[PDB]
Length: 266
Length: 264
Image (cartoon, one colour):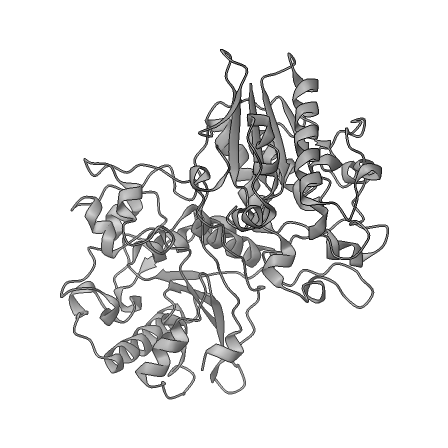
């Protein structure tokens, strides 16, 4: 048995900055493509385009990262029997595109688990992002399981949550995920956040969590699609981090370029 | 008539650093893949793997950057009638993958022109990179024209070249490129270096070049696949930079990750 945990792909809001909505949406709040790193379309959301502010999508290159990981899993014959993700759109889109690369997009149905959402301290304000429900995610051609009953529904998350609460629910939900997949296929994939890789696996392995200051510093090191593997040893039944079955993915930037501001014109 | 000039895609040596060869090659100099941003294979080179040191390939993401641009050109209904590139492998690979996006890889044949190589002061040492000749590039399934007769062959390049020489030969070669494509298709694509966007278009437009320092500082701003367009106004015959027919491409990094070092 193996638990794979990885981070979502490149985020639109990180690339395109504080006012990224202005690069993606017109005066009427309709999506527009102003860069090749943006897709042809984005889902309509119940509260309009500003719902994207606390729940940004991945980029085209975010999609490509996800697909490269899926293809690498396929190429290594790493069979994924179940896939879960955080309700964050970026996590759902990442999971969908791993499935594409895996060529399992018509077989695997992604189980959206609010339990896997990151520490709610990272959310601005006193309300949660307006996550797109699984029924709408499926309507947007993301391979989500609309029949999945989450272990920690949105109703059970609080924005006030302590670090301890975040680690504890991550431990709790990870055990419930493993428990329900037992004897239903060896490999489980979680697609979530930078913080998830340690939060989902720390107490699973019997380890004590770090203090929150060291935790936050560490979490800043997890690249997009950062990928870890936590295996259950048959002999002892103990879970332990091990080398993933795929190579790491590393690439650099392609910076912003305005030809008028740079090339000689006079 | 339009002249499009763009930079090659992401470079393998830039991503993986000074000791990048150690990440791509084994004790016998055979290519090894140790990262998903590395391709499945690299061409066999006459002087072995160290020839890559001064002539690095593009990465997987460099290829994807190239194909995206090609796809955008196809979507914009922009027809590329001729394509030229620097002999740098990164430029050739980028040009090929642009053709892939255009779905023109079996019709267009890339014209490898050493005149489009960048300022030779960016080459370490006193010898040029051991560029892979067109017949070998074709053998590696890159869509290169093995019959193209370059306007500035490798034999004509000087490793010790001055800035003014680089700017002048860029002007010279661009004019000769334009002249031989006249009345045989309206749009020309040049796939080369950061420095080529300006060097190839400056004097073409009748402009005075910047000094070498301001040139270098500007050159540092040009991203991978950075794309400009220089159009010939039909009324006057004056060439001028204009808005490209495709959107720009901007993305961030996905840095290194050692799970042993970072995770509990």
